[PDB]
Every structure is written in structure tokens, then in C-alpha cells.
Length: 205
Length: 205
Image 1 (tube, one colour):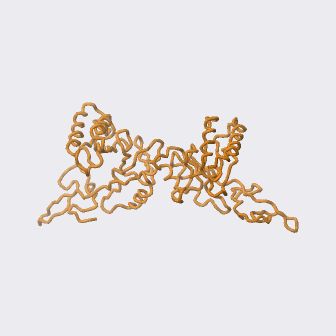
Image 2 (image 1 turned 90 degrees about the horizontal axis):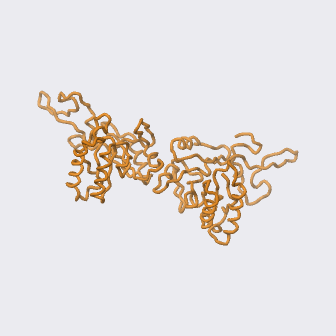
Image 3 (image 1 turned 135 degrees about the vertical axis):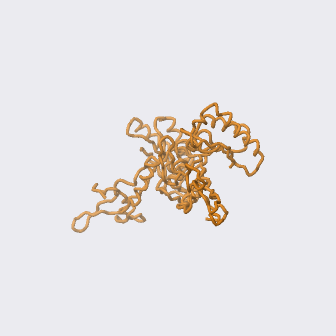
């Protein structure tokens, strides 16, 4: 799944830029250059419009642009609540199997519910699920139970492959794994950089 | 829900008569006379084509006839596997909440699965569910949990209201409740006549 380099996650609201005409040139270049570059790979199955940037008109536009230019692949976008008109696939992040999380504005349904909501005909693939933050993946089996049982639950992507930790050294010259804040970077989000299935040295959790 | 007086349950296969042109006159009269009779009631919400008679061409025809003549109500039919083209409502019998029962030919999906099957857009209402045979209704809460959670699960009908037992008398002139076989009727299906929420005397289980 090949994602455009666009994430405006820290904006308030998230789509402050992606629903703003003036940034559409910037965004368009990011998307269009990506597509032109990777157009010919066979491994690339799905185009993604980016990540967590809310849902704005610029997404709708760029969705359509890709569909126009490369009709051979499907386009995915989770921002806006997984199921806006700028996605071919219902694609949500950390939606639970049997539990609805009715957030104001952008409710996050259970994946089983989501499929059946009046009008939903698309496939559902979990953009991000199962948050592997250290000692985790509890209940992982539930997802795979569901994936096998339901036809339109077509899998998903575990978050994520490898811990984003950095090596620092102690006074003896020994190396150790550093997380947010350990370089004097402040504010930071501490251990949240490490959510891998494998360690940074590619040994496995 | 007003049902036409048609059930060919004991046929082999069940639709032996209902897919046979020559019985279409008989069937049509049953349906059409019913509709003409009860057309004007406000309590009548749904027309039903009958019960457990498989799925044959005669159902398709009669479905259409009703739709033509009384477009103000919806038409329901469970035979054939709850979701044939002769029904406006996915309407199944004893489909379990979270358990698929993949029967040859006419699989009976879990109701949660059923809603989401590629192409299903209709509402789902359980023709018959929760079989109240004596000391029963175990797990009833699961249905109502589901009904409240999913938008297209719109309830169902419990099977059933009152025990079909008959009074017989002993040598002292005392009355007692009789079930299949107690009148010398053989073969019979014994206690299966009693599946009520209330007793035949309308006291409650």
C-alpha cells in the first residue's frame, strides 16, 4: 500500500489545511509525483491518500485524480472516519471487533457493525489495528476469528513492524535504546515511538 | 404480520409443489383471497407468503402480485433460505447470533454475518427465533444485545406465544395437558406442540 506523503495530524481541526484551497497545490504535488513514480510496480496494490489529515475537499479532488489517471488500482483513505467518499475501502484505525466507540463527529464502530451500516457496500480493511506497544497484541485472535468469518473483512495492517528506538551511549561506551525525550527533545511522546513486532535490531518480540 | 395459508413443509424437496405450475392456481387463491380480505387493516404491516414451503417460481409470482396490488406494505418470505428474491426482508428462522450453521444448499448464517454478505441491503427480521420449548430462552439476551446494536437488525418474532396442549381426562375426571401421541395419534411429534411463553391456560412460564 503506497501512501502519499501527507499527514497534518497536529492541526486543529485536522482538516484545517486539507480543506483549504491554497494548500491544494502542495498536496497535489505530493500525490501526483508519488503516483507517477511508482505507477509501474506490481507489488503496489493500493494507493493511499495519506494519513490522519481529516477530510477535506482536497482529498476528494485527489482521490478523483488518481482514479482518473490510474484506474487499475483502488484508492484508500482513512481520514475523516474511514468511510468518506474519498476511499474505495472502508479503512479504519483501531476499530474494535465487537465494541463500538461512538466518538462525537467521527464515531468508530465495531468492524462487524461497520460493514452492515445502511448503505455500506465497500470492503473493510483495517488501516491500523492491534497496537503492538511493547507487551501487547492481547485479543489479536479475535480479529483473525472475525477476518476469517466475514467475507468483507479482508484483513488489515498491524501497527507496526519495528520499534523506532535510537541508540545512545553511556559513559562506558555501551549502547542502549532511547525513546522520546532521551535526546533532550521536549515536548515528546516518550515510549510511543516503540510499537514494533520486532526490536530495532530486528530480533523479535 | 399476516401470513398466507401455505405450508408444504413435509414435501421432498420442500418446493416440490411450490415450483410446480399446476399448483399455482391453488396457491394464488390462498394468497390473493387473504390480501383482499385484510387489505384495509392498519395493524397489518407485512404480508407474508407463507411458511416453510421451499422456494419455487410460484413464490416469485405471488410476491410480485402482492407488490403490484398492495404496494403500501412489504412482503416477507423465509422459505428458500431467508433471502431469496421473493422477499423484501431477510427473514430467517433460528439463525444464531454469532454462529454460522452452513447447511448444504441453504446455509443459515449468523445474523451478524448475514447482514454484511456482499450484496445484502435488506433489513433483517427474525421470522422465528428463540425456541421457547419448555424450560428455554437461554441466551435470549444475546439477541437483544445485537438488535439494539445493529441498525439493520430490526427485531424478530419469538417462537411462540402459547403451548399447544389439549385437555384430556383421567379416570377421576381430572384434566391434564396432553401432547402429541396422547390421543393415539401416530406418528406424532410428542412435546414439540408445546413451545409457548405461556401455558395453554394463559398462565405464564
